[PDB]
Amino acid sequence: KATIPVNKLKKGGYVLIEGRPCRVVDITKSGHAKAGIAGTDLFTGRRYETHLPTSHEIEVPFVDRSDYGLINIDDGHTQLLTLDGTLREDVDLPPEGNEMRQRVIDLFNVCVNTNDQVVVTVLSSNGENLIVDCKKS
Image (cartoon, one colour):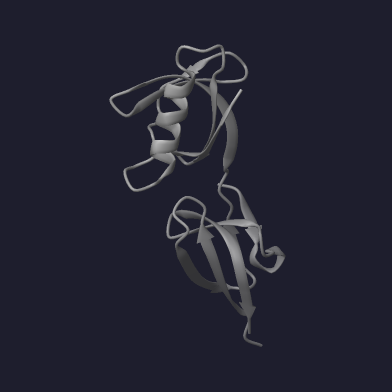
């Protein structure tokens, strides 16, 4: 459990609010010493907000953004090759309604019989994984 003093928070830092990893977008401060923190959920874009004592600390989530080679897609699951040479099978395609789902399927199909490979960018935190970009390699 990594923490930062609330009084050391900056806009753009990462915090956990209601279990959600967020980028800080606004910090308000008040003998009384209380703070209001608003953030953007790194996966869904939703606004979250919390109020804690300024003296206190707040949890900072670990968030990874890495690139992988897309080996297969099957029943909505992906098989990915890390840049260090191992497979991961816990990343699904983005959900229906996220246009990235079609973008990844289509780029995979453009590449499947060619000497190019799709590279996906995956955002990961606390067991949640989302494909946030794709490009040709």
